[PDB]
Image 1 (cartoon, rainbow, N blue to C red):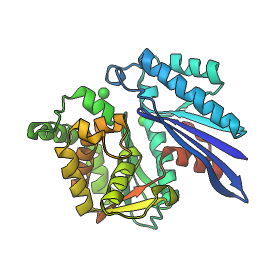
Image 2 (cartoon, helix red, strand yellow; image 1 turned 90 degrees about the horizontal axis):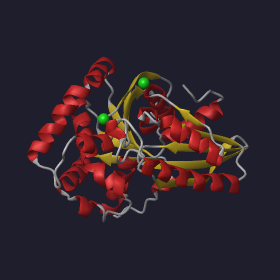
Image 3 (tube, rainbow, N blue to C red; image 1 turned 90 degrees about the vertical axis):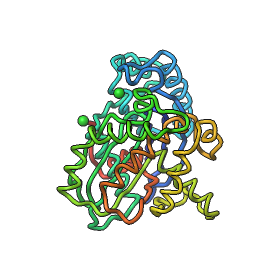
Length: 312
Ligand SMILES: [Cl-]
Ligand SMILES: [Cl-]
């Protein structure tokens, strides 16, 4: 039948609708909407009224699109901003009343697992031990695995909206800001360092909006005739990453707002995100970065198609 998946992310909500004919899935809708669920509240442990109202607006629109495609099987996941918010049940109950969708709140571990199922479908890793990283506005998930297995995974509440709200990063970034961020990452990421030492991944994979934007910027810079919508991976060399890093660290918020595809909430957090990627790169001896165009919503879909329960 047709399957609809909603990812209620901290910055951006996503809607994926897939038809599955002759056991082959085909995308009917892949839509996003900037919601800013974390704005004004995430580091203080709540969701604001304005953010809840934006969320409901977007969900009313997504409900129309679901109905316009006669979708029967729907699953809507709530992740970092939803699970973190003391008033999450207010939002969940408003959603049920307004559009008759039940939000499935998933913890960080399960979010990481589901993301990696999407990565496995997008990037054929063979037996290569790989570190995948998903940077969102609220959390960052890290998974070590290969085509068949997850060896280790962990979610950390260090998504970009949290980072820019908890710390004062200057516009543009200063040397002392770089010290601040990498010192913080040193403290937070100890379990990641330990896992990397244990499993020795040899490749780095990134997914979600920050990585999609880096890919799109690189495509434009090299004048590549590549629609990222029509392929499931994109390899970014380390020299290309370092060009983008230098460009974005030097940039102002206003300059970033002018980059094609760089939505406002991503412009706000992309510099701290690139600092985190650099930090992780120094821990791995990868040869390049592979961007997976699949992330949580695709992992949910493929988990469903596998015949496996999504929640937990
Ligand atoms: Cl926080
Ligand atoms: Cl967890």
